[PDB]
Image: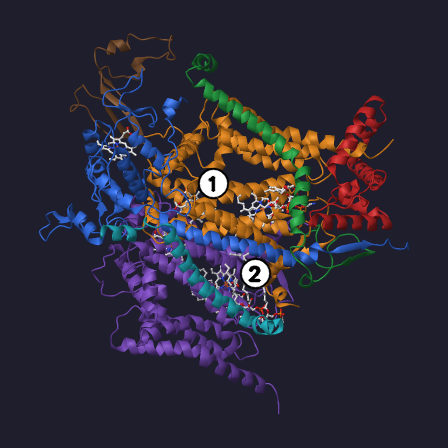
Chain colours: A brown, B blue, C red, D green, E cyan, F orange, G purple
Amino acid sequence: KVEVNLAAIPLGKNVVVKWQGKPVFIRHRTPHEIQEANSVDMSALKDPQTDADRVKDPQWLI
Amino acid sequence: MTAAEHGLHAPAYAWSHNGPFETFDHASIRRGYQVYREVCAACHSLDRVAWRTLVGVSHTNEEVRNMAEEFEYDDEPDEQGNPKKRPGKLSDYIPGPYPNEQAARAANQGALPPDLSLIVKARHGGCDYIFSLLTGYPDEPPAGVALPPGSNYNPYFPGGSIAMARVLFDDMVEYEDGTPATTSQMAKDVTTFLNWCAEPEHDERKRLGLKTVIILSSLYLLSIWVKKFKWAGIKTRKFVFNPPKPR
Amino acid sequence: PQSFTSIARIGDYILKSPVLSKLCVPVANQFINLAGYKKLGLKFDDLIAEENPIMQTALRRLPEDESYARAYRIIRAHQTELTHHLLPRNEWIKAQEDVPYLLPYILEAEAAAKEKDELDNIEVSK
Amino acid sequence: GPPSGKTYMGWWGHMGGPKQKGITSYAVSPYAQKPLQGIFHNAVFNSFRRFKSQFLYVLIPAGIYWYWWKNGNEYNEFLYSKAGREELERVNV
Amino acid sequence: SFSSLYKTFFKRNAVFVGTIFAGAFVFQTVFDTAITSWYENHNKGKLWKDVKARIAA
Amino acid sequence: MAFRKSNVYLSLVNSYIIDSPQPSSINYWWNMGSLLGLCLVIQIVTGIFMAMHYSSNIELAFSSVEHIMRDVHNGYILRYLHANGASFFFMVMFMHMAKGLYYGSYRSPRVTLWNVGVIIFILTIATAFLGYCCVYGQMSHWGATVITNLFSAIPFVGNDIVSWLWGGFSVSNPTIQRFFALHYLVPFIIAAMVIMHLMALHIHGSSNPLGITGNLDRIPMHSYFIFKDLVTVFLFMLILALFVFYSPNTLGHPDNYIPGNPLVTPASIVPEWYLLPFYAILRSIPDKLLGVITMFAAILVLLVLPFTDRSVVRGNTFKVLSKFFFFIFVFNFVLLGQIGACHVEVPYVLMGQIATFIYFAYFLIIVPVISTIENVLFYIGRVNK
Amino acid sequence: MAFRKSNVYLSLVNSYIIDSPQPSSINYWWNMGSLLGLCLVIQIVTGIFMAMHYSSNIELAFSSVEHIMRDVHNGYILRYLHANGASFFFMVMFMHMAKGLYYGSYRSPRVTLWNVGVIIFILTIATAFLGYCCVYGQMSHWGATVITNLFSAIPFVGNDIVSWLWGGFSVSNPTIQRFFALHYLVPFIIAAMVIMHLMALHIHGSSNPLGITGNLDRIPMHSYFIFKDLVTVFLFMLILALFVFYSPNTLGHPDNYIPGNPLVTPASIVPEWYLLPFYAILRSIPDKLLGVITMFAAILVLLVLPFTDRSVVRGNTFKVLSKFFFFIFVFNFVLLGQIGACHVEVPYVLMGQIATFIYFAYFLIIVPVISTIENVLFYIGRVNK
Ligand code: HEC
Ligand code: HEM
Ligand code: HEM
Ligand code: HEM
Ligand code: HEM
């Protein structure tokens, strides 16, 4: 269980950390596509999904 | 998949070391070391090749001693414990331009230049791929490609978009034997040097292979004769059968 | 491991039918010719695999002259293929000579073994 | 040790074949023979006899599978070309 | 005279395998020299001593 | 009696390689066993002389392999000999198994010999996979990842056994040190199983290409089959020397000269060429549990073979349909190996599914039907009623 | 017949461990062999499960051993089990050999069994020396240097064979990686030699403490000697669990917890306790070439024993002088082992020289003279004239 964290991260840039053999997005969440993310498809896609269970943080994706 | 993302296949050039009795042209290895040191060493590294492997292959002893002493390596610390530097010796390895992966990715717009000490064994195509890649930069990327910024077009590279610009231009390196350093001349020499760096055993491997193939084909034919000799009595054996009288 | 009673039952049903005997026997004769065991001087009953108790009883009950002829045909076949040749064309086993000779012995040993294993699992009707 | 089970091969003297009568075998010393006798005749006539006997069995399935592989390879090359994308989408999904 | 040849080279097995070992010794040495001279001669002007004699003039 | 019989050990040597009665009719396909024994000795000796210089950490595996290739004397000879010798080992083993499947060597007296052979096949597949994984190139990391990650489809226990195989949470330093210790170990288990292979062989002797009994004339193994073995020994050494000294990297993949990177997937992950038919069999099932079951059943279908061969004649020497469908099976195996090296694309998945079906219908559908048809043809061609 | 006889493999298992006719008179000293088999299986299994975590470079050897101790689950159990099981293997092997030369088991039907035993003893000594050298402590390193610089006494090729052993110029990374590959390898040669030990035993069967023939009443090995061996197996596991769990670093030296340092000598270089008598034999001779010749002679003098035993009855069960001088030999061996752990100070060099002379005079002087004297006493005590 790595504990990498957030207060030294602004947005304008991605982080893709890798740990435990894990390459993984971590990024602050924009307003712009916080509701492009709530603008989405539901099953005109392959993805009947919920951004609430996907990203429980409103402001931080990983 | 599409031939774009496959990459165009490199053609078969007539390398002077292709062939079972052939040897690396050592003058082209010496010139290719010059092409590496003056152009390729800005981005790529060669950390599997010690300095002492160059002696008696492409340079003399004094030349490799001077080329090693023009660099600085880490020494063991002094009696006070402070770190100390050292001019290079023959035992050391050829240093790369960047201290880590992050300096490389920072200086080359995200991409990391691969270490070139095994790159002709690590690409399908061998030396032909490296030559076609170095000389295969068109002046324009062909009609309709969405080239990302910072990327260049090279059709031999799988996908097309390579993060290395064209680095070989004519007469950018003067050779000390007076060879006309065109683009293809420099690409030929640096590809021969990279092939030596990948396979430094090449000439002795082919010489020992000549001895071994001669001795083993001698032994194979001679064993065919000895088998036919020892088996002649069983091959030329005759059977007659007179049915016995019933009792 | 197909029992010769099964082979004989299917084969006799083929041979006593009018229609499919005249269809299925020419393809069988072509199969026998293309097999090419006769070119090595072998009848077919030399080809049956003998490492089972049915064939051991049949080869023990085979008469003495047939066993000597079979032993010579086997030794000649081994000597022929050891040299990677064939027998000359006057030494090939002819079609009237390729008889089933071991087949009645195999059939009676198989009937005896099937009767034995039916009697070992018998159940009286009480 | 104890004797083990009944096998189908004994040793020299008690192999386990049938009794043999009337078979006489003759053989000459290899030191009195010519090895490599008939190699230039067997190399051209016997080789052709063995090839003629056993080549339809090997080369009819080889022809079938090589034609199948070439046809599948040509179709895969066509599907990822510019001329054959409009079949590739309705082929895969 | 094949009889004298047989009686001095193939009769005893000790002198037979001694001749085999002496022949293997001299064969190994002169076979290595012959292969290395043909290899260095087939690759002429490509070897390092050729390149070194060229840059030494 | 002679001292080669009166002794404890020399009578074993005598009884197996000196006085052992072989059928006189056996051809050059019967040299593959002696060839596989020579191959095993080659692999063990060169592996010991490279493990004297190999380091097995995740940091030092690749660079220790190039330390073998670059600065230890004759180390390129040892590594190219070990790698191409493993590939030649698998080619000769495929010839041994296809000879046994052609000539009916799996049949009624020699089923224990066939089963110990199948166990040997499984163990050397495992050994070659682990030894590929010890190189720690790019192909070996992602091959280890795919093959180890296939065990996650076991529905209750699969995550625990893949974490136990890895020694962690992905292929890393524990996994590479585990795989080195096992790749060192399993060849001695293979040598013990080869001794048991020979012990099961010795009780009934070899078969012969006629399929008829060979108890009638037999010749000892010494000075006949010793030299007939020596012919193919020198031929094998010649072809291996060609592949070691003139094309040492032809049978390999060039991606293993990239050091192993967990962060870059090489866009076409294939194993070594001899595992490619089983890789295609695994890939051609649109599932994961059924895929791993189908690959293991493809290795274990060779045990069903002595019970589905329904013919009274041992071997395919004198049958024409069995010869035809045997070579259909052989070139189906070759097509399956060629399909396993191709991408998941459109014609290749149907070709892989049909070739998998042909692979399994050979042992289970084609061989019984064809052999009983041949039995009835052999009968009615020569009896008259 | 029964299936345990009518098989190939179960025939061997039956013939060796189930229906093996043992003499009924054999006491508890005839369990040391099955005990050595258990010890060998313990060493091989625990060594494999530690080689899954051992790294063999000179900068990683010692710390990989402590990684086994501190980080691997139950790894202290594995390391302490391997080390104390190696020492227990040698105590049981000394008991096996002392039984053999007490009860006359070396004698004329069983000389090849005795000689295969001596080969096994030499191989186990080599295996344990390499395995002690793999841990790379301070006694490990300096033990490696003094034992390998023994071989520089050969006056022609000594420097080149020691530079071939070292892989360089002193004990460093090639030497340690070599010693790991060999310390794996030689145990499987020991397993092959144990199979040959059993084969040489099985032709004539085991002896008995009376020394008379045991052909008259015999007992199958199953259900009698299986349980009589189970008694000593549980006793041996009990005593080993005591030393592993309550007293683990007792037999070891404390200086193997200092990492290996080529610049600091630890002021008393001694090997593990079981090689101390041969170390004292080597130390007693005031020359190095004669020292190694005398140490190898001290272990090759077990081969002159079937030719210097000059008596007509086998064993020391019914002789008084053979019993007395046997226990003089055994406590001479224990004094030699205690002399080998002391410094080269003034009474100890003379004590080691006299004890080495007694060790050699036992085999070459004492056994013939005492055998002849006991022969003529047995004669004239009961014949009248
Ligand atoms: C400056 C920055 C340079 C210079 C002067 C050279 N190279 Fe090249 N190179 C470079 C980058 C950033 C990359 C990565 C591009 C990518 O996306 O992969 C590369 C790549 C290569 C490769 C690999 C091609 C492949 O992956 O198939 C080879 C081979 C290579 N470079 C060789 C090379 C040679 C021989 C040069 C001689 C002067 C050379 N490079 C110059 C960055 C740079
Ligand atoms: C059963 C026989 C064996 C087979 C089939 C086998 C197979 C392989 C293969 C395929 C490789 C990868 C080579 C490469 O691609 O570069 C390999 C590597 C290796 N094997 Fe083995 N091997 C065998 C026996 C052994 C044994 C017994 C040892 C050890 C004593 C050993 C030690 C090694 C080592 C150290 C490597 C390291 C990488 C290298 O140098 O190639 N092998 N093995
Ligand atoms: C390490 C690998 C192997 C070795 C050393 C080995 C060794 C041998 C040897 C020496 C023979 C006798 C010579 C011969 O008949 O060719 C033999 C026969 C045989 N082997 Fe193997 N073998 C190996 C692998 C296999 C495999 C993988 C199989 C099949 C699954 C197999 C099945 C057989 C069969 C069926 C025979 C008998 C053939 C016959 O005589 O009819 N073996 N083996
Ligand atoms: C013949 C049986 C064996 C003997 C007598 C033996 C003996 C020894 C000894 C005395 C040590 C030093 C223990 C210490 O002081 O720490 C040792 C260490 C070692 N042995 Fe063995 N060994 C045997 C079998 C094996 C085998 C087969 C392996 C490999 C699979 C092995 C792997 C090791 C390892 C890895 C060490 C490393 C140091 C340690 O963990 O203690 N051993 N061995
Ligand atoms: C790995 C080591 C060894 C194993 C597994 C082993 C195994 C055995 C076994 C199981 C027995 C039969 C049971 C017994 O008599 O105690 C035996 C007997 C014997 N062993 Fe060992 N042994 C080993 C080492 C040695 C050594 C080092 C020698 C002596 C040089 C030796 C000489 C003997 C003798 C002479 C016998 C016959 C004793 C008799 O029954 O009268 N063994 N061995």
- Label 1 is found on which chain of the structure? F
Q: In the shown orientation, is residue D13 left or right of residue F84?
A: right
Residue at horizontal 37%, vertical 26%? B8
Residue G199's label in the rendered image is 2
Question: Dot 2 surroundings within 10 Å: few (below 14), some, or many (20 or more)?
Answer: some
Q: What residue would you read off at disc 1?
A: F126
* E19 over C117 or under it: above or below: below
Q: Secondary structure at mark 2?
A: helix
The quadrant of the rendered image in which ligand 1 is seen is top left
Q: Is residue G243 above or below residue C4?
A: below
Secondary structure of the residue carrying tag 1 is helix
x%, y% of residue B34?
A: 22, 42
Which residue occupies the foreground of this view, E13 or F354?
A: E13
Q: Position of residue B97 (x, y in %)?
A: 19, 38
Give the camera-side residue of D59 and F271: D59
Kind of residue sitting beneath label 1: Ala
Is residue G147 among the parts visible in the rendering? no
